[PDB]
Structures are given as C-alpha cells and as structure tokens.
Image (cartoon, rainbow, N blue to C red):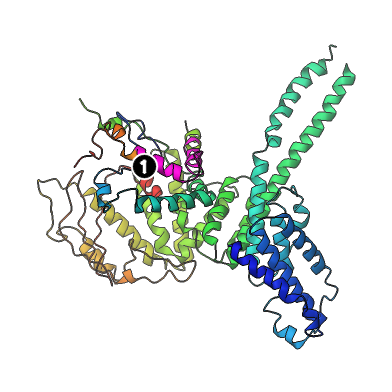
Amino acid sequence: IAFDQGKLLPIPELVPFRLTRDIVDGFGVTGVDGLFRRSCERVYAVLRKDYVKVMCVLNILKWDPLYSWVMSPVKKYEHLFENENQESYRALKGVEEKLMGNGLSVESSVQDLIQQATDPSNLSVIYMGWSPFY
Amino acid sequence: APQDALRNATLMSKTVKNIAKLYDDPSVVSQIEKLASFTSANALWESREYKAPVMIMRDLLAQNEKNISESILYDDFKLLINVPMDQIKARLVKWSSESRLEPAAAIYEKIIVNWDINVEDHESCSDVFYTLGSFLDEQAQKLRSNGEIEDREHRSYTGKSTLKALELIYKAKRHYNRVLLQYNRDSEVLKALLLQKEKFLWHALHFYLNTLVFSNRYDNDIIDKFCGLWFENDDNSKINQLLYKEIGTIPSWKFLPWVNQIASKISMEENEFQKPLQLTMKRLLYKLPYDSLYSVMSILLYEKQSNKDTNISQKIQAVKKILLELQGYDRGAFAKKYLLPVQEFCEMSVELANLKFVQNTKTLRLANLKIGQYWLKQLNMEKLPLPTSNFTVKSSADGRKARPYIVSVNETVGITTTGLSLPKIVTFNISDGTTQKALMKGSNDDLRQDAIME
C-alpha cells in the first residue's frame, strides 16, 4: 500500500492502527490509557518537533523513482467474488498534514486515533482482512 | 536547557570583571573576554531576545576583525592555553549568518558576507559548512517557488499580446515603444532570478560536499539533503560539470541507503549528471562488491525477462556495459572473484524460485539438495559473501572481509509451504554464526514496491 488506497476497496479499511481487543489484551490492566498512550505521545511529539527530516526521507527516496503510484487492476477488487506525478504529490502532501497537524497539542491526535481505532462502529464494516474477532 | 545554563553564563560575567588586574597580560586577557562574550551570546540565544545575541555577535565579530594585536608572542601561558579556547572567526561569522536569518531582519544580505569565508583546515569547519549549506538551500527553494519565477508567464503573455495589439497601433507607436523597453526589462529580470537560483544551489552543493569530506557527526542527515539537491536539478553543466570535477573527492563509499536509486538511473546519454552518476557507481562497485552487486544482479535477472520496455533495453546495455568495464578495471577481471559467484548465486536463487512450483500434495520436497546444485555452490563459495544479516563498513573501512565467508554450508532440507504458492527451505546452515536459516519465497507480486518501503 504505502499510502492510503485501502481507504477504497470493496469495503474500505480503517486507517488507525488495529488496536483491537486482543492486541490490547497484552496490556496488563489499564489497557491503552496507561503506558501505551504515554509512549505514543512521546513518539508523535518528536516527529512533529523535527518534521523536516521525515519529509526529506520520503522526498529523496521517491524524488524521481521508477515506483508505481497505485496498482488497481490486480488488487483490491481482485479479492471480490461471485494522475501520475500528481498522485505522488498529492500523497506526499498528506504526510505534512499528519505531521504538525491542525488539532495540535499532540494529545489531541493521539486521543482521536485511539477512539477511531477501537470504536466498533468502524470495526463493524470490514470484510475479513484481519477478521477482528478471534 | 537555559533555565540552568544561563546561571553559569551569568557567573562567567561576574568572574571576568577583573581579569586585567589578575595579571598584566593584555595579549591574553582580551582573548578571555572574547570567549566570555561569545559564550553568553549563545546562552541567551537559546532562550529569548534574539536581538541581544545578534548585537553581541555583531560587535564581537567586528572587534575581533579589528584584532589590532593580530599576533604577539604573548605570555607563555597564553601560548600554552591557546588551543584551549581561541575563537575561530569563521565560526563567529557562521553564527552571524544564522542569527540574522532566524529573525527576518536581514533579508538575503547575508550573501554579501557569505562569499568571503574561505574557512580553515582542521575540525569544526564542518559545522560551518553545514550551516552555510542549510541557509543556501532555504534560499534556493524560497526563490524557486516564488511568484517572481511564476511571473515569467505574465511576461510571456504580454509579449504575445502587446506585440500584436499595441504593435498594430490602431489607436500610438509612442505607447508601443514602451512595450519593447519594458519587455526587455522583464526578460532581464527573469534571467537574473534564474541565475541567482543557480548560484544559491551551487554553493549549497559545494558546502554539503565539503561537510561530507571532513566529518561524520550528522552526515546521516546530510547525505539525504545532498542527494535531493543533486537529483532535483539534473539539467545543466553549471551544476553537473562542477560536481563531476569535485564529487570524486568524497572519501567515503556511502550513498548505500539509496544505492538502488542510483543504479536504476543509469542509462546511456552524452549528458552531464549521467557522467558522475556512472562514476559514483563504479567507485562503489570497485570497492564494496557484495553490497552493490546484489542489486546489479537482481536487475540483470529482471531485465532478461519480459524484455519489452524500451527503457529496460536501454538499462540492460547501460548496466552490462559498466559491469564489463568493471572487470577490466579490476586488473585482469580480478573482480570475477565476486561477480562470477554473485551471478551464479543470483541465478541459482532464481532457479530455486522457479523450481518452487514442484507441485505434489507434499509440503517438504527435501532429500537434501537432491538435484539442486547448491550442494556444490556452498563448497565452491568457500568464502561466501553474506546474503543479509547485519553488516557495515560505516563509511569506508574495509568491505573486503565478513563473517559470512565461513558460510560454506547449506543444511539442505525440506521446503517451507503453507499458504500462497510455495517457498524454499530455511537451509543456510549459517556461517561462523549458528543462525541465518532464512528461506526465499519467490513469485512476483510487489518486488521492488515492497523493498522500497522497507
């Protein structure tokens, strides 16, 4: 995937990390709101603080690559049964939105992703994929 | 943080008030004061009041430039301690360039000073080059994206329309005469901004290049920045001939984090850019065989199949040509010691992937190698280059030795299989180490598309 894409599909994916019920079961009481958020906040804050290096890495490795920007004919709807340089630009700019952000204050991003990640209102959409049960 | 550091910056002032009275040595006490002023300027800058460090540094610099007593035997003590402090005006200038730009109160006037610093030759000059390079990049991009460059379109529109309607002068040639004069001024201005763009760029490259020659403290960041500026402007001789001439100075053999993106750009053209691109490639192939050869052998395997693209055909010849030249460069195909084996290994691996589709209802297919020729290959490769693991030369060092040489073993065994397709046996039999045991699972799928994300 690399960027987005799974947001399409014959039933789209949830972008927030799959903090489903078993993954967080490994958090020994006080799941998510304990050590997990604290670690997340430090990491996210650092990335926001330095910023430029992240964009640099992506920009160099994919400055003028031979990389394919989204293959659809053999993917996504492939599992169903019964732009050019503009895409590069558009996708890379989304990085700048996740970095820095508009919600600001760090915590706000972390809290938002968590609610989205665990809310069954979104989980109860997905076809198989990880099959968020078991 | 400053909440602590400022206390000492303050103390230093208290402790130097009478240095002229501790001993009668004008030739050193003035130097001591310079140190103290510098130190506090930085302590302040780190917090707030950017206005103060800049004045401190501007005045300190001017005073140091006005050394007056540019040299003296000075006290023997001064000589003894000379290397313990000094100052380095080159460093002071750097700090002025930065102090004047962090706030906007200097526009780009910095350039009037910038060109003048011819630095020194020891250490810490790498900080100086680094900052100068960062400042040139910011200016180059601010200009590149400026409306002033975009404005060329307006000048073009005026040229197309005024040349018709005003030229027709259906209703004064006197007014039309202004079109030529103003148009010529517009053209000269557009030319001029493009020239500045190139000068900022060239010098930025020069400074990053120099930084990479003398230090390894933050080269981890510089190399990406350098690559960017170079690949960003793969156009004229103004940048590329100079790099061809200077880029060969890089004492290291790094670039590795994106060697795949270097090698893939090699093609056949008479142009600059391609020349130093190819030159760099040879530099690395010659000195660090195995760390470059896997990507080369990989592309050659790729190229031989589905040879439909016009670009792949060109790539084949470009790569093949270099590889043949490399055995020439080796001495007498000395490098055959690596290439023949690498080619054989790559071909064997390709065969294993192709042979993965052994069918049967089984999930084994062992009998050691049985028909596999790896049995011979593990022995022929009595000094086998390392597939993966974790290995580096840091910068240069020596890429001719690795633990993996003692990997002349295979542990040929049953293949992994489970879900999609089929895979190889872990095999490996490690080396000096007792691990490895990593199997292949060839198919097609994403290939390069996954590797790049990793």
Identify the residue at horizontal 42%, vertical 63% (top origin): B289
Quarter containing the N terminus of chain B: bottom right
Q: Quadrant of residue B128?
A: bottom right
Residue beneath disc 1: A114
Provide the chain ID for the residue under circle 1: A
Residue B37 falls left or right of residue B368: right
Q: Nearer the viewer, residue A60 or B371?
A: A60
Q: Is A115 a magenta residue?
A: yes
Tell me: residue B13, above or below residue B424: below
Residue A91 lies, in percent from the top left, at 46, 37
How many residues crowd mark 1 within 10 Å: few (<14), some (14–19), many (20+)? some
Residue B60 lies, in percent from the top left, at 78, 65
Q: Is B330 a magenta residue?
A: no
Residue B216 falls left or right of residue B419: right
Work out which residue is located at the far top of the displayed protein and give it.
B170
Q: Quadrant of residue B347?
A: bottom left
